[PDB]
Image (cartoon, rainbow, N blue to C red; front, side, top):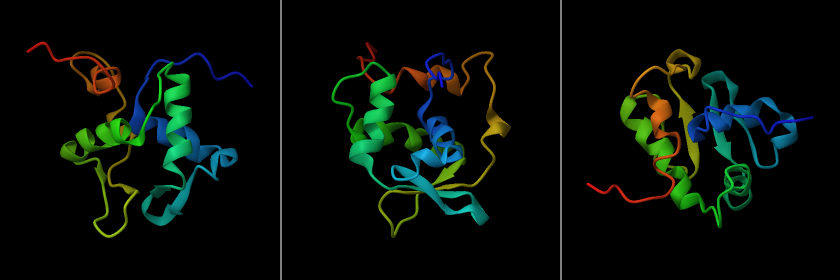
Length: 118
């Protein structure tokens, strides 16, 4: 029961890791497995886990969704208009699971904290 060693350090992905484990249902479960649709049961709590293992502080859902959004542009996830915290996995996640250069990974510890110094 050891899940400390990580690498991807990604949010959008952090989702699956949870879904797979039913023990994390109360926080998040599969809405419509038919279309790999998931929904955050409780953001206030769900985020905690994301900010906890991330050694972050006062991890809020606001600064969290900041990621899922970036992907929305890549045409990977779709946020239903009606619902509020609904996410639909259009394309397979493992399809874009890689790390060579300027890959999604890069955005693992970027949209979390720190200026752009641009």
